[PDB]
Amino acid sequence: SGFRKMAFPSGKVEGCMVQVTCGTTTLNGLWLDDVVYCPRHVICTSEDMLNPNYEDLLIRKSNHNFLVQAGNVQLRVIGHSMQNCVLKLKVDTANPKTPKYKFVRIQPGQTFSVLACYNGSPSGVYQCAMRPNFTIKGSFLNGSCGSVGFNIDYDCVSFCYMHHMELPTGVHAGTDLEGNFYGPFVDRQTAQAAGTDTTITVNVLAWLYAAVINGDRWFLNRFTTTLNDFNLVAMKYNYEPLTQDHVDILGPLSAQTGIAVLDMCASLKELLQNGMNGRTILGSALLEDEFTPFDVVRQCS
Amino acid sequence: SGFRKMAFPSGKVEGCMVQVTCGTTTLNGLWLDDVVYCPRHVICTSEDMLNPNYEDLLIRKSNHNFLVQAGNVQLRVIGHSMQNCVLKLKVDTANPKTPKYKFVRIQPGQTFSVLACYNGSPSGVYQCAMRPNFTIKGSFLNGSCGSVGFNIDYDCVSFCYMHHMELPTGVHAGTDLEGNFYGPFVDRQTAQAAGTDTTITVNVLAWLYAAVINGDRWFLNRFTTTLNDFNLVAMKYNYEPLTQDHVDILGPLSAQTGIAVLDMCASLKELLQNGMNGRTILGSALLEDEFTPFDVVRQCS
Ligand SMILES: *[C@@](O)(C(N)=O)[C@H](C[C@H]1CCNC1=O)NC(=O)[C@@H]1[C@@H]2[C@H](CN1C(=O)[C@@H](NC(=O)NC(C)(C)C)C(C)(C)C)C2(C)C
Ligand SMILES: *[C@@](O)(C(N)=O)[C@H](C[C@H]1CCNC1=O)NC(=O)[C@@H]1[C@@H]2[C@H](CN1C(=O)[C@@H](NC(=O)NC(C)(C)C)C(C)(C)C)C2(C)C
Ligand SMILES: [Cl-]
Ligand SMILES: [Cl-]
Ligand code: NA
Ligand code: NA
Ligand code: NA
Ligand code: NA
């Protein structure tokens, strides 16, 4: 049946993206009800961003400084406030294409679909994990700020990410829709380091079930281990500790394949000590850690 | 700025997906104007599919055998015809969410976004290449038939794939919207083999430019080669021959990075003869061949 990195359909989110412009600076906004959310550095010049004072910059702006465009339709801004690092523009018209939506803050390890946008126009959609060090390995050009990360539960859009900035080596940082950064980052153009990144162990295990579901069985061994013995080896290879909550959450996949989680931990223990000896798993020469159990159940059922 | 496998936003296509049911058998349809396109084996029982006679099966059906559902709204079928392996249901209502659309037949090597659907409901979106042997490495469960492949040019949806069936090892086959199979395949449940798959050389080269754009330079060498010398080595590793049309098409990327195509061919020649000596390129331990030049320009500009 096959296994691909797969994103949520982007339609409901597409109908929310607008272009916010303040002077020269123009980026993307999320239009929900009568509010446009965007990163607050839309009110900066290239120089302000080297060491901004957003409060100072925003007092100086009036409602009229803000050009919001939804297609060929302008939008009268009739208010503005700043929630942490996001800007909130009250507008005369409520968005008729506003879906049921929630704002959530995701945990490191959870995945989400990025709708990458330029000039308030949907360009493309891909899947990302929130890394342990609170970065994402996205793909963002200049103009992509405002682009959002989301998940869908049935009809409800769970917005969890808005893109702000890029760190050394094409890794990325942003906020929830409360305007709170993920990780210890600030919307200021000064040297900031990420913190070492770990491998999301529960996610690798989820992917090995995907592999088995799909007929890749070669790594399966006749052993189990204890959580304790497994975590002593994993710690050495910079894998996250596997908790009992991780085991419980892997339950469905264990049930779908009839392979106990501690048997699959036996397989992973061996792959870390020996590598793959020139062997692939779902076509990858590396262990893949950006598929959650919830992603695997979804796509393999 | 980063480099991810990225799909077109799926909104315009989302508004076209319906559920077609004939007896027990129910799959997805594409609703465009007053026509619903779906795979023709919707009129089969599990047993008919072992050796169908579609003409015989379809004569027996009347317009009323066909249940088309668009949300909670049924749709009066008022006609039916069969174009090769696709079924065309004329319906009383033209789809108001019908985008500008084209039907195109893609070449092996070209990429497209799959909108994977179950019960006429968009489930997820991913990117695929048409392989040299006219298969795709998709992810499709039972119920996914009718799901479509597309590209977007500005406002125009270029529909090129409709999913029919799965071959040995989670590879997939389908038709254009004329109902013509890609590859030598038939919509019948009997043993069929794929034909050996080659590596899309021009696509690997496109991806190496992506790598260089993104700061992965380690494989860059001080050599050029001739097309001829390169194709003599590539032929041995089951890489497609690189044509002058391939070189011409790589032009923009060569221009964006100031690396001649025959210099990058010098790099690739070395990677095939030596492998990567435990080195990654954009995080991959393998050479990636499912990004077209047109995909790389897009995402790296
Ligand atoms: C901005 O949001 C936009 N309108 O697109 C933009 C996003 C993209 C620029 C290129 N890649 C992107 O992700 N964000 C910025 O330009 C932010 C903005 C100003 C600097 N900045 C950056 O992303 C810089 N990174 C940076 O300073 N990194 C450190 C690790 C902090 C040194 C830049 C050098 C431009 C990529 C703020 C307000 C942070
Ligand atoms: C069908 O379109 C649907 N309603 O979902 C379905 C698609 C998915 C089944 C599982 N994976 C899919 O991609 N297609 C079929 O069931 C088609 C259908 C009947 C058999 N068939 C298959 O895909 C089979 N493959 C097959 O027979 N492969 C050979 C190489 C030809 C032996 C099956 C064994 C069910 C996966 C036709 C009309 C071909
Ligand atoms: Cl993928
Ligand atoms: Cl990817
Ligand atoms: Na103000
Ligand atoms: Na105000
Ligand atoms: Na008939
Ligand atoms: Na008829």
Image (cartoon, coloured by chain):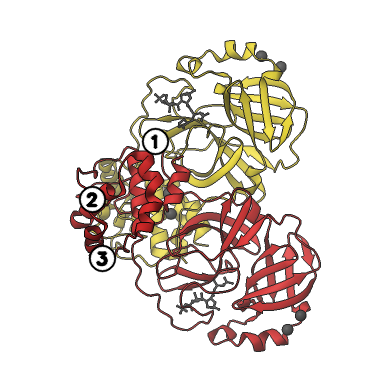
Chain colours: A yellow, B red
Report whether B97 appears left or right of A208: right
Which type of secondary structure does the marked residue at label 1 adopt?
loop
Q: Which residue is mark 3?
A: B235
**Residue A156 percent across, percent down from the top left:** 66, 46
Q: Chain of mark 1?
A: A
Q: Residue B129 occupies which quadrant of the picture?
A: bottom left
Where residue A132 sits: x, y (%)?
Answer: 40, 36
Left or right? Give the position of A157 relative to A266.
right
Amino acid found under the numbered disc labelled 2: Ala
Residue occupying the point 43% across, 60% down: A254
Q: Would you name the residue on which mark 1 appears?
A: A170
Residue shown at 58% from the left, 49% from the top: B9
Q: Residue at x 19, y 50 (%)?
A: B277
Q: How many marks?
A: 3
The reply to whether discs 1 and 2 touch (Cβ–Cβ < 8 Å) is no
Distance from the alpha carbon under mark 3 to that under mark 2: 15 Å
User: Which residue appears at 60% of the width and 71% of the height?
Assistant: B178
Identify which amino acid the numbered label 3 is placed on: Met
- In the displayed structure, would residue B16 be above or below residue B89? above
In this rendering, is residue B31 above or below B125?
A: below
Residue B67 seen in render: yes
Judging from the image, mark 2 belongs to the subunit labelled B
* Residue A84 position in % (x across, y down): 57, 21
Q: Residues within 10 Å of mark 3 (few under 14, many from 20)?
A: few
